[PDB]
């Protein structure tokens, strides 16, 4: 219902009273998250510039502050000591120049000679509203102040369409590389385009990374290369991916692909996995960004929200949030994702659990529930439930002969993008034990399965009084329930 | 230099781009606090509505978001689990009605039947810009949403001037009371006016609290009654207080007065102390608010900033911050002030200290330094220092025969309200040991002396590279230095 004209009106054409009212409405929503990054107002999308710089972790965010829609985008900035306690540093990059006149689109951050380079796509729209994507390298100093150049680092080559964006800038084997999401103009196929530079001034196009003969959709958004336990891992968003390659149920998937080896000079990838896999088996994860931190870990964080989708909170004039930070690991040829050790510092009021059918009559809105469930069982765990278990988030489990987890949000509250289904299923090994580490925060749930072998992340909109946690049947398990303190 | 017209322009007449730019400028200031409450933009003053409600601590703030000046005021809202980790809930009360058309001035919060009543002064200005102060009772619900009535609870009586504000609403001995700061129309003397109600609907004026025959200045701002270890304690701001009653060096003082007994029905106070005393011996504390929490403690928090004063950060378009929360105690007939136990959770990188002249060559911008210094010594402790100790915050101590502490900020950076002096002195007991617990955060320093017997709080603006901590001479002492994590 918001027209193009309304979405692209400049921030200076909105009044400040409207913005202050929107900040109040977002912060005081009964569906707001209070230990995950969320918008101060309006809509949040893709994580950007995820980095370590000047003694702390940095994270930037795609932002449209005036409503629950993809209006003209800016970067906002947060920092933290520990990947958990974030503090807001305000807007960072505005759509205020010719290069970015219709948005400061997504990008990355790389430390260089005591500064943090912020490489992003300028979403230019010309006199005729034709999109011309520019790749821009801005610079942030040790006081978090940003300067932007007058000229693009990379102009769009003739062989890509208008879709050519989301640069990842990094240093590898003494050279600089940029990975970009690209649509080939002739085939309309999705690719990761590689550029290289010795000096950050002149860029050479090495060409599309060779990901085999099968198409990766019609566009790749938010490509990332991170090294995890010495393996090159791609994390990327192939819009229109053929489900023959990999099943997924969300409108657009967020995949990962582990390589044995990558050669960015020759645009070669040697796959470890025969096929890419879903990063997240849940309902709402997109635009994951990852980076290699100086502690020797690779960290990722996800937009919880999908393009071209709607949510029940739209009428409250704000949208979406982030996942918690995930530390990455490769084990047994698969990507594992772990909560960072600092998130334990939010825990309070520990309860020990042993075989209790009702875990809590009323658990509050922010908790962590960690369970060890025996093999050979079937049943349902209800979270954010009413008393009679008819309205809840359901985790339907079987650890017996047809083992699997089905997460069902149909009865949890109002419908959420129901054209893409109200259930998500994760196969499990027959007759094996099951670990769950479940984080609830307002209208966000993150389920870490079998110590991070799988992660299911989703929005859900339960009535405020629906806080019960219970199994439907007597279940053999041990675990702990903690409240999680508000920090945001 | 900001005219009346500019200060009173409605928030809707500012553009949102200006507000977003101001949020960035405030948050990224190299003088910003990162573990104390600070404005998201513009100017912060008096703490308001300090309370416990709906499972958490609440604090509201006088705010003018558009610059470093006392423009037309609103309340903003923060909450926390622990009086340390605050999260922003946005604007709460706007100057958007006839009752508060020229400001939502200060006030208090009292829980009532599952709601939080917010009692505040409406700063009305009529057709002729004549001030008419109204006392208004607004109501907040369990989702932090506020409704405001159409009519005032208390209209200004004929015997007070236009200065009649800052209501403290509370329940005591089964009745409701309101304490207001008042200027008598005939004498132009400062008073605390007492109102009482059985139902919160009809208010009866009990009259000025009898604080003896000596005048308490020309106006009392921000009056508070809190019960501390069963003593009634007044905390208040008597503008124009005669220094014959008590020495103070700040433009306007923030005093406290312990009573043996108070009778709010008869407007009687029985003093324990012969005279009121300074709450804070430093350079910048004003408008302290306190309340009795359900854990049985009394807690206070202070505006760090003074009316009618200027600061070096004014050119960065933001102003001021809060103190940390202080837990109150009465000991030996004096008010002691203690950090809350939760602030220890910010500590990291502990260093043990024993007699070292140089504590740190470079301590960072956020730390806690706790020292035990032997009796019989004299010297200077330099904080936020250059290498040669010529530019620093100085704590000049003597624990020998003329014992005292002098805090000197003259060489720390640019001048700060120098008409009110660059030193503050606290007498100490001759030939006694000295405890200091010093918190540095950006441009804020809080010095807790002798386990909270005195507190000195000040702004200071050191060069970013001035981070040395050192004694000028060999000094006998033990202590600890911790870094303090950013949370805001
Ligand atoms: O907000 C704009 C950004 O969002 C995406 O469409 C993915 O969600 C990116 O390709 C683009 O940079
Ligand atoms: O911001 C307005 C408030 O500030 C004071 O002048 C004290 O600093 C109060 O008496 C008034 O309510």
Image (tube, coloured by chain):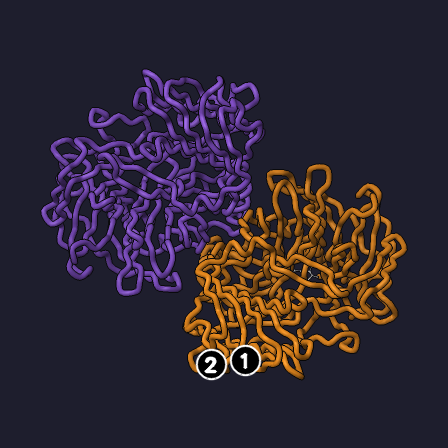
Chain colours: A orange, B purple
Residue position for label 2:
A389
Q: Return the disc, 1 or 2, that comes first in the chain's sequence.
A: 1
Q: Residue beneath label 1, please?
A: A380
Helix, strand or loop at disc 2?
A: loop
Instruction: Please say if B292 is above or below A312.
Output: above
Q: Quadrant of the N terminus of chain B?
A: top left
Q: Are marks 1 and 2 in contact (CB under 8 Å)?
A: yes
Q: Secondary structure at mark 1?
A: strand
Q: CA distance from mark 1 to mark 2?
A: 10 Å
In this rendering, would B103 be left or right of A171?
Answer: left
Same chain? Circles 1 and 2:
yes
Q: Which residue: 69% across, 66% down?
A: A279
Q: Looking at the rendering, which quadrant does residue A463 occupy?
A: bottom left
Q: Residues within 10 Å of mark 1 (few under 14, many from 20)?
A: many
Q: Position of residue B298 (x, y in %)?
A: 29, 47
Residue B123, visible in the rendered structure: no
Tell me the quadrant of ligand 2: top left
């Amino acid at each position: 219902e918001w027209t193009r004209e309304q979405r692209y009106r400049k921030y200076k054409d909105w009044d400040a009273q409207t913005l202050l009212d929107l900040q109040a409405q977002a912060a005081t929503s009964p569906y707001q998250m209070h230990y995950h990054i969320h918008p101060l107002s309006g809509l949040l999308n893709d994580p950007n510039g995820f980095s370590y710089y000047n003694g702390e972790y940095h994270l930037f965010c795609q932002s449209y502050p005036f409503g629950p829609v993809h209006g003209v985008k800016s970067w906002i900035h947060f920092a933290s000591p520990d990947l958990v306690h974030w503090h807001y540093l305000g807007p960072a990059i505005d759509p205020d120049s010719d290069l970015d006149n219709a948005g400061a689109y997504s990008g990355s951050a790389m430390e260089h000679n005591g500064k943090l380079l912020l490489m992003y796509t300028g979403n230019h729209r010309d006199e005729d509203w034709t999109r011309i994507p520019y790749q821009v390298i801005a610079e942030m100093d040790e006081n978090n102040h940003i300067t932007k150049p007058d000229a693009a680092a990379i102009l769009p080559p003739e062989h890509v369409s208008e879709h050519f964006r989301d640069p990842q800038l990094f240093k590898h084997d003494g050279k600089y590389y940029v990975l970009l999401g690209a649509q080939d103009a002739e085939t309309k196929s999705g690719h990761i385009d590689i550029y290289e530079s010795d000096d950050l001034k002149t860029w050479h196009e090495n060409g599309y990374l060779d990901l085999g003969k099968d198409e990766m959709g019609y566009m790749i958004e938010c490509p990332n290369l991170v090294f995890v336990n010495n393996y090159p891992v791609l994390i990327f968003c192939p819009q229109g991916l053929d489900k023959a390659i990999s099943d997924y149920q969300n409108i657009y998937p967020n995949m990962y692909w582990i390589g044995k080896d990558i050669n960015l000079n020759e645009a070669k990838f040697t796959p470890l996995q025969s096929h890419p896999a879903n990063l997240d088996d849940g309902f709402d994860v997109y635009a994951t960004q990852a980076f290699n931190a100086p502690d020797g870990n690779a960290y990722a964080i996800s937009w919880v929200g999908l393009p071209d989708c709607t949510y029940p909170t739209d009428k409250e004039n704000w949208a979406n949030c982030y996942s918690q930070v995930k530390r990455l690991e490769i084990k047994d040829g698969a990507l594992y994702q772990h909560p960072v050790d600092a998130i334990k510092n939010l825990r309070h009021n520990e309860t020990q659990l042993n075989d209790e059918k009702i875990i809590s009559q009323k658990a509050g809105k922010q908790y962590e529930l960690k369970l060890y469930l025996a093999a050979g069982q079937a049943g349902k765990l209800h979270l954010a439930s009413n008393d009679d278990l008819s309205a809840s988030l359901v985790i339907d489990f079987n650890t017996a002969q047809d083992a699997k987890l089905t997460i069902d949000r149909a009865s949890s509250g109002p419908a959420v993008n129901p054209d893409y289904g109200a259930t998500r299923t994760i196969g499990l090994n027959d007759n094996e034990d099951l670990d769950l580490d479940i984080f609830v925060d307002g209208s966000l749930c993150e389920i870490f399965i079998n110590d991070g072998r799988h992660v299911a992340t989703l929005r859900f909109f339960a009535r405020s009084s629906n806080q019960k946690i219970a199994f439907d049947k007597d279940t053999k398990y041990t675990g702990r329930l903690w409240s999680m303190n508000s920090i945001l």
